[PDB]
Length: 54
RNA sequence: GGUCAAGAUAGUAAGGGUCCACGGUGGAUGCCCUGGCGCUGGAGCCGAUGAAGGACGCGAUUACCUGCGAAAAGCCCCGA
Ligand SMILES: [Mg+2]
Ligand SMILES: [Mg+2]
Ligand SMILES: [Mg+2]
Ligand SMILES: [Mg+2]
Ligand SMILES: [Mg+2]
Ligand SMILES: [Mg+2]
Ligand SMILES: [Mg+2]
Ligand SMILES: [Mg+2]
Ligand SMILES: [Mg+2]
Image (cartoon, rainbow, N blue to C red; front, side, top):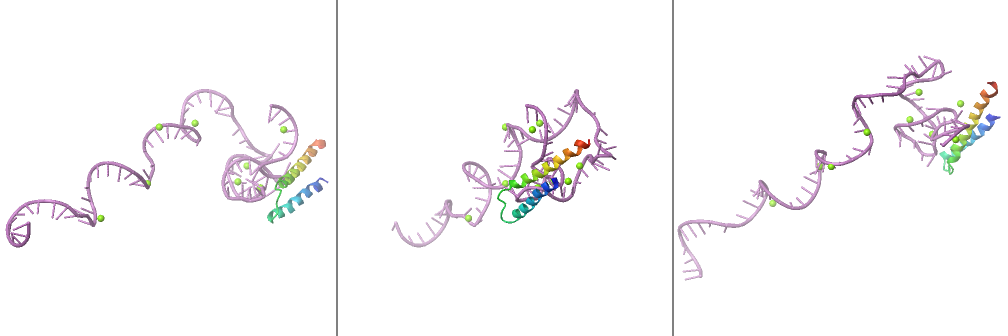
């Protein structure tokens, strides 16, 4: 399911990128926030790798 | 006074020269430190877990440097 959680931020980042290429990018911060949420969402995966499996 | 003769002698500067006054150019000199030099003393290896050094990228807007690496001027934990 974590891939499902990731690609939603991906698609919003894509359509938001399109909007930036056009005439409307009124909240630039929503960009890097979404990128944050991807990094976090992957970093958490790393913590379930070594945990449990040892 | 006036003609006539003889004689002497000034001022004109086209442009120049010396001096002065005033500027332009140009970056010496003084002052300054963001940069260096040396001695002393510490510390002294890095890499197949990918080194040293690079290439390409990551910004709302990014050409250069800096930082980073598709999780890309950052992500998690701890302390101040
Ligand atoms: Mg003249
Ligand atoms: Mg000059
Ligand atoms: Mg001086
Ligand atoms: Mg110095
Ligand atoms: Mg390298
Ligand atoms: Mg970028
Ligand atoms: Mg660069
Ligand atoms: Mg990846
Ligand atoms: Mg903290």
